[PDB]
């Protein structure tokens, strides 16, 4: 039940304009496709919807969770939405016939900074580019001018689209905001705005955080909700998401028995704790993702050779220098995965660069990074990454980050292999388990943590990864005694069931 | 909202016939071939299952084979702000219109014989102007007019 | 000049079958459904009169309907300067090739169910690369592959 | 027949298929700046001097640089009628 289910029940059954202030990650795509599926299920008319993001990887993820439809829905980025729905069909009507239809969007060499010379370029040499200042949008201004100037654009964009789904409004240009409340106010289109407020914004350099901070305090005509994506899936596991160390201890409900926790004998080894739970108890599954989040890397590698003598061959990726908090991890990880694997496609690298929709020009950067395929380990990485970041924009996000990227391929391999294919039985530490979710989390008692009254946030964020099953053992008698003391401190008699 | 007229410029027995239309049209008369050819012209314009077979040699007047078959249908498109099927057409037509002719829409069908493969190809165009009609876009076996219209043929 | 292989990735009883081909191919065996479905897959790829009807629910494996039907045929295109049918393909394919892959050509068919109109649309692509295949252009009821090929089906 | 189907093959992938033939504003008068215009701002026009042709020079360069343009233009056309 609790906040996840009641927020889901409220948000799904709404019909008005919705504003969702969520947290960091935790499946915004899940609530987005659930609301999209509910809205498409309840509607039997001819109208369609438009889902809007920045990266088209999220677009193919959204249509993968959605499936197939021929109703006419638009899934993609806002650049493609403005290009194919407002600019291209009505540029010949809004600004006379002498303005041209068939045109190419290219924002890699253009740095002009006026509207007049911009539509002079669009009339004479028919190239649509970008503004010089990062906090502008020539395309959205042109779309707003087309919508205010052309009747048939208003008729089409009112007669086709029913709801518009905006994501990542925390980093959004003010021209996008102007076009979106113009679509909301006059043309009477419903809006589903999701996002998070402030908390270390990145992506699409030039963010204007006061946009999303403009419709939290002063806005009135918006049904507002907090985070609806759960911290943990299922129901019984969420109890320890409310544990923390203080205050939220009061917010947790009482239960006489929790079915999602299994406690076992501590005398025997885990390598057949797994064999007892999978075979004799039929609790765990080898074919499901089976991950122990632990720390103290020397005993982790000890567990590794113990498990290779067991036979299932657990794999370890440690904390890379790339794994530190940086605004540019997500693209250079794709660059290194395309370079050092051998067969990764260039469109998989193309799927993350800012606004994408880049045709005919992927070879300009694949030539540069194909020049990066020479090993040449001494000094060529600096200038080829320099001309790459001149090519791909988001400049001067480097110096420390170029060294963090350098230390990955130093010695030609950081860990001899990397996350190349899909394999099971992975192990992550607390420095790198954030972001990627695990089906079964089998922490193995969080060795010597609870009775010390410290190391508690580490096993808490270890338990944040679990979906359906998590196991906590009393590995020590004083560990069980401190568990009993802590559950006296909760004023709750049972939070853990031992079989 | 409301149909305006149909011009049949070449068919099995039509030379150049301009019939004013409306909703709820009732045809009658003495010769049954002309009435069933009127209904077959409407089916060739609007039904996908009949259009996919194309034209034969016998679908031209006098089997003359050297004349282009043209069938044009006009709509009113004017009664907006209260009507639902207006939006049903506008949402699929997209940018095939002009703001000067906000009303009146045209859907047209053209055909010319091949005389070597013995096949008459059917090409569909639409637009709000009498000339400069553009082709109806479509991916595979279907186009946008199949998404617009649904034709039910009732015969005992 | 010479066919290379056909990969059927979904059909009535084909899961993923990669059959090497040539000119003068002879198929035989015990079950007749698989052989007649091989010939029907070739007819769906290359014959216009069978492709125009589209796919039904029964043309997918296990009637599962959620899987894309893919049929790809590969050619050699290498034996030039002496062959006539090579020119017969290059004259119609036009600018769908690359000079790096002067040899080897791909013709592919894709299909995906609609689940609302109960109709499987058939989309044809071609190109000299395994990815970035572009759609075959066509005006009305025909496309360029109908101008290339002529299929004769002989059944007593 | 020569420029549009094979521009992306003859002069690399970074050259555009899409272009518009406009010869009322263009008066640039070199080959180098001409294909700079055709690459960056993707307009094919005319020369400044009247007794020149940028389009036919580009067609000759595309035909001499691309194999498949030669294969297509030999395998399709049989006779060419000049008036």
Image: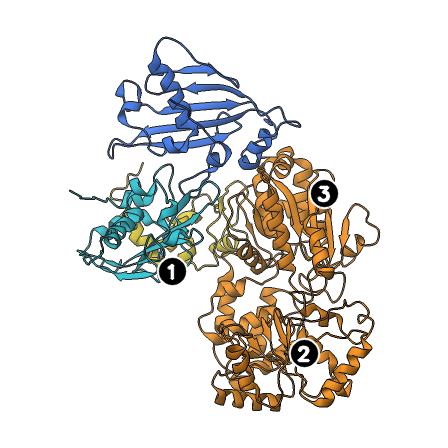
Chain colours: A orange, B blue, C cyan, D yellow
Contact between labelled residues 3 and 1, with CB atoms less than 8 Å apart: no
The x and y percentages for residue C75 are 28, 57
Judging from the image, what secondary structure is the residue with disc 1 in? Answer: loop
Residue A87 is at least partly visible in this image = no
Judging from the image, what secondary structure is the residue with disc 2 in? Answer: helix
The x and y percentages for residue A263 are 64, 80
Quadrant where the image shows the C terminus of chain A: bottom right
Q: Quarter-wise, where is residue A211 in the image?
A: bottom right
Residue highlighted by disc 3: A184
Q: Residues within 10 Å of mark 3 (few under 14, many from 20)?
A: some
Residue highlighted by disc 2: A400
Q: Is B89 displayed left or right of C89 in the figure?
A: right
Are tags 3 and 2 found on a single chain? yes
Quadrant where the image shows the N terminus of chain A: bottom right
Q: Residue at x 17, y 56 (%)?
A: C26
The x and y percentages for residue A417 are 50, 81
Q: Residue at x 62, y 24 (%)?
A: B79
Residue C111 is at least partly visible in this image = yes
Spatial CA span between label 1 and label 3: 44 Å
Q: Quarter-wise, where is residue A447 in the image?
A: bottom right
Residue highlighted by disc 1: C130
Spatial CA span between label 1 and label 2: 41 Å
- Closest to the camera, between mark 3 and mark 2, is 3
Spatial CA span between label 3 and label 2: 43 Å
Q: How many marks?
A: 3
């Amino acid at each position: 039940m609790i906040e996840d289910e009641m927020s889901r029940e409220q948000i799904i059954k709404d019909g008005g304009n919705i504003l969702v202030t969520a947290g960091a990650g935790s499946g915004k795509t899940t609530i987005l496709v659930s609301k999209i599926e509910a809205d498409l299920k309840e509607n039997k008319t001819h109208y369609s919807i438009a889902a809007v993001t920045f990266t088209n990887k999220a677009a193919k993820e959204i249509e993968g969770r959605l499936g197939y439809s021929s109703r006419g829905n638009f899934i993609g980025t806002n650049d493609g939405f403005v290009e194919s729905e407002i600019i291209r069909p009505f540029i010949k009507d809004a600004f006379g016939n002498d303005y041209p239809d068939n045109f190419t969007a290219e924002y890699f060499d253009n740095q002009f900074a006026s509207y007049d010379k911009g539509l002079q370029v669009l009339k004479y040499q028919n190239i649509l580019g970008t503004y010089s200042n990062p906090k502008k949008n020539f395309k959205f201004q042109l779309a707003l001018d087309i919508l205010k100037k052309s009747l048939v654009a208003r008729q089409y964009i009112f007669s086709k689209y029913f709801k518009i789904f905006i994501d990542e409004y925390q980093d959004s240009d003010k021209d996008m905001h102007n076009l979106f409340m113009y679509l909301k106010d006059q043309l009477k289109i419903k809006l589903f705005i999701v996002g998070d407020p402030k908390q270390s914004i990145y992506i699409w350099r030039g963010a204007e955080p006061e946009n999303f901070n403009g419709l939290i305090e002063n806005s009135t005509d918006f049904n507002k909700y907090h985070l609806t994506s759960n911290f943990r899936c299922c129901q019984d596991i969420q109890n320890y998401s409310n544990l923390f160390n203080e205050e939220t201890r009061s917010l947790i409900k009482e239960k006489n028995e929790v079915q999602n926790v299994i406690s076992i004998a501590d005398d025997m080894p885990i390598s057949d704790i797994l064999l007892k739970l999978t075979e004799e108890k039929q609790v765990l599954n080898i074919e499901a993702e089976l991950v122990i989040l632990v720390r103290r890397r020397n005993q982790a590698i000890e567990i590794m050779k113990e498990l290779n003598e067991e036979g299932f061959n657990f794999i370890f990726i440690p904390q890379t220098p790339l794994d530190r908090a940086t605004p540019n991890a997500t693209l250079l990880k794709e660059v290194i995965k395309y370079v050092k694997n051998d067969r990764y496609s260039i469109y998989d690298l193309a799927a993350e660069i800012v606004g994408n929709l880049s045709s005919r020009e992927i070879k300009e950067i694949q030539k540069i990074i194909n020049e990066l395929l020479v090993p040449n380990i001494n000094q060529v990485l600096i200038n080829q990454v320099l001309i790459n970041l001149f090519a791909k924009l988001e400049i001067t996000l480097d110096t420390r980050e170029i060294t963090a990227f350098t230390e990955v391929m130093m010695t030609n391999e950081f860990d001899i292999a990397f996350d190349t294919n899909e394999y099971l039985h992975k192990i992550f530490t607390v420095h790198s388990a954030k972001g990627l979710e695990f089906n079964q989390v089998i922490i193995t008692a969080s060795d010597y943590n609870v009775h010390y009254n410290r190391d508690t946030n580490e096993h808490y964020v270890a338990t944040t990864r679990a979906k359906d099953k998590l196991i906590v053992i009393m590995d020590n008698k004083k560990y069980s005694d401190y568990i009993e003391t802590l559950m006296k401190e909760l004023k709750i008699k049972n939070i853990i069931k031992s079989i | 909202m409301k149909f305006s007229n149909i011009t049949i410029k070449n068919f099995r027995n039509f030379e150049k016939v301009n019939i004013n239309l409306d909703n709820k049209n009732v045809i009658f008369g003495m010769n049954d071939i002309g009435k069933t050819n009127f209904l077959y012209a409407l089916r060739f314009l609007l039904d996908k299952e009949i259009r996919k077979f194309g034209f034969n040699k016998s679908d031209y007047h006098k089997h003359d084979t050297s004349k282009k078959i043209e069938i044009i249908l006009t709509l009113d498109l004017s009664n907006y702000e209260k009507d639902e099927d207006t939006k049903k057409l506008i949402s699929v037509v997209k940018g095939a219109r002009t703001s000067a002719n906000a009303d009146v829409f045209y859907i047209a069908l053209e055909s010319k014989y091949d005389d070597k493969e013995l096949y008459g190809n059917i090409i569909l165009k639409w637009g709000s102007e009498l000339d400069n009609l553009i082709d109806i876009p479509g991916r595979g076996n279907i186009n946008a007019l199949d998404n617009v219209f649904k034709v039910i043929y009732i015969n005992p």
